Image (cartoon, coloured by chain):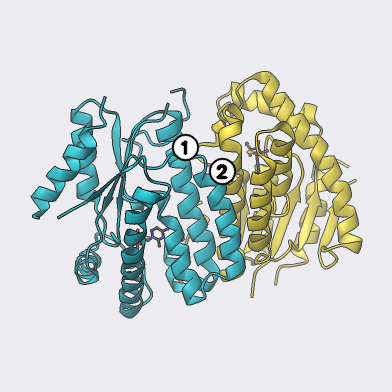
Chain colours: A cyan, B yellow
Amino acid sequence: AVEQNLYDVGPRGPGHYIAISGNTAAGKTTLIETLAGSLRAAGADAVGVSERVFHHRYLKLMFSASADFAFPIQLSFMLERHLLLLDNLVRRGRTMVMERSHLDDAMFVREHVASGAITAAQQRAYTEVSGELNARIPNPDLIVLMNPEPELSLERLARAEAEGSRPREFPSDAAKRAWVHRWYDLYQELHDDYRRRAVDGDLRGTELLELDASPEEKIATVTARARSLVV
Amino acid sequence: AVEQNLYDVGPRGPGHYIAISGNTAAGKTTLIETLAGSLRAAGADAVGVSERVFHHRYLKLMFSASADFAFPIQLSFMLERHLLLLDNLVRRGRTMVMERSHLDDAMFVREHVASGAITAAQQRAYTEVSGELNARIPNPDLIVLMNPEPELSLERLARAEAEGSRPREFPSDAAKRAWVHRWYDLYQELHDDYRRRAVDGDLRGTELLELDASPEEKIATVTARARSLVV
Ligand SMILES: Nc1ccn([C@@H]2S[C@@](O)(CO)[C@@H](O)[C@H]2O)c(=O)n1
Ligand SMILES: Nc1ccn([C@@H]2S[C@@](O)(CO)[C@@H](O)[C@H]2O)c(=O)n1
């Protein structure tokens, strides 16, 4: 994040905002970094921001001590993503390729409300702050719907945990599988919502990209649409 | 903070919570570290937490770009202090000597509301989240009222900035002096409030310590009262 100059408070409209949307529980770091690189090649000051940037040091406690930590850790995801966008995209006019946009955090609170880890009153408070924060951030310019199947997410996650490339964030194998499945199910509904909101809701000025196709064809399609934005 | 093991998510009622309250714009790091050391000497797992632990990387923008950054940076102070207390004090039962408690953050939002940097609607949202967060954190056990005069805060700050021991967080000398004076004035009112709330409000189970006396006498008085808590 220091190499990407994400946290520079020095002097400098907004830049461009590209976001993946889907249950990327094992991450899309290669895709967002390759995409940001292609935008740099075209002349943009572009950075690919993986969710790991927003992992609070207390992240594991959201899953092992959910009734206590899910609310404040969800506030953290929203707040840190907000600040990073407000500084890099809005204030400094940079081009952001995000693993997840500010529109998708509320779904993760909904999951914890349904399990009882976040109370209805906590959710109402979250929604009031989220409304004020999101009103200051532009909608993404290009949203790419990419929701992999849970079995694939879980195979990738299991290999990464076994090889030590990321910590075991969940308190049991079953809890890992359950959270990943709950997020997948919620993302199927959110993606149906996206198709409506892009046509008849608040995203009419945003390009919504859905993918057909090999992984090479998918990267090529996303890159072509993102490059339409580079000035 | 790594030496103090502040961010350990491993396995383990709450511990003890001692807080200074006042316009410590130049910091009370020596006092809180000496006090935490005295509690360690008596056998407590005690740590002194200065406000620098909660300085967001974007802190300077609260003062140079207040209309955009004061709201989310104030959310950050509240949230990070909340999480640190929820983990260290509540979950892990450690003894926390805080430069500032969770009860004092709202005053800093009030300052930005009065200047127009935070809107009334943003403040209402902040208050709703703050109420939910604070309901999960015990009141401090010992609160020490220490509000130095602004001229002293500013002399200390000027020397620290000139010697490079901390960054210049403010966009002009006048803005630094103005914020420090506004915080001092608000803290005089908050300290009047504290004297009422300790007797007839929500702090009746807390020891409120006010200081007469040399700096040596002040440290000795605070240390004696904090040591009454070490088991
Ligand atoms: N608002 C959010 C955003 C992301 N995530 C998790 S945290 C993670 O990146 C760990 O690798 C992955 O599990 C995401 O699903 C969340 O719980 N809440
Ligand atoms: N909720 C809060 C808590 C602390 N502070 C400032 S940040 C500081 O520590 C910089 O050294 C000092 O200026 C404090 O007064 C704030 O602006 N808002």
User: In the rendered image, which residue does mark 1 sit on?
Assistant: A86
Point out the image quarter for the C terminus of chain A: top left
Residue neighbourhood size for the residue with mark 2, other residues' Cα within 10 Å, grouped as few (<14), some (14–19), many (≥20):
many
Q: Relative to B159, is B196 above or below?
A: below
- Residue B93 visible in image: no
Query: Horizontal and vertical percent for residue B46?
Result: 62, 60
Residue nearest the observer in this picture, B19 or A59 = A59
Per the image, label 2 sits on a secondary structure element best described as helix
Q: Relative to B146, is A149 above or below?
A: below
| Residue A88 location, quadrant | top left
Residue shown at the point (87%, 60%) measured from the top left: B198
Query: Horizontal and vertical percent for residue A189?
Result: 35, 65
User: In the rendered image, which residue does mark 2 sit on?
Assistant: B72
Residue nearest the observer in this picture, A36 or B86 = A36
Residue nearest the observer in this picture, A12 or A7 = A12
Is residue A101 shown left or right of residue B70? left
Give a yes or no on whether discs 1 and 2 share a subunit.
no
Q: Relative to B113, is B90 above or below?
A: below
Chain assignment, label 1: A
Is residue B222 shown left or right of residue A170? right
Residue shown at the point (59%, 62%) measured from the top left: A124
Q: What count of labels does the image hold?
A: 2
Residue shown at the point (48%, 41%) measured from the top left: A83
Query: Horizontal and vertical percent for residue A148?
Result: 22, 63
Amino acid at the residue labelled 2: Pro
Amino acid at the residue labelled 1: Leu
Residue shown at the point (29%, 33%) measured from the top left: A46
Task: Kindly check if marks 1 and 2 are in contact, taking CB atoms under 8 A apart as contact.
Answer: yes
Point out the image quarter for the N terminus of chain A: top left
Chain assignment, label 2: B
| Residue A23 location, quadrant | bottom left
Per the image, label 1 sits on a secondary structure element best described as helix
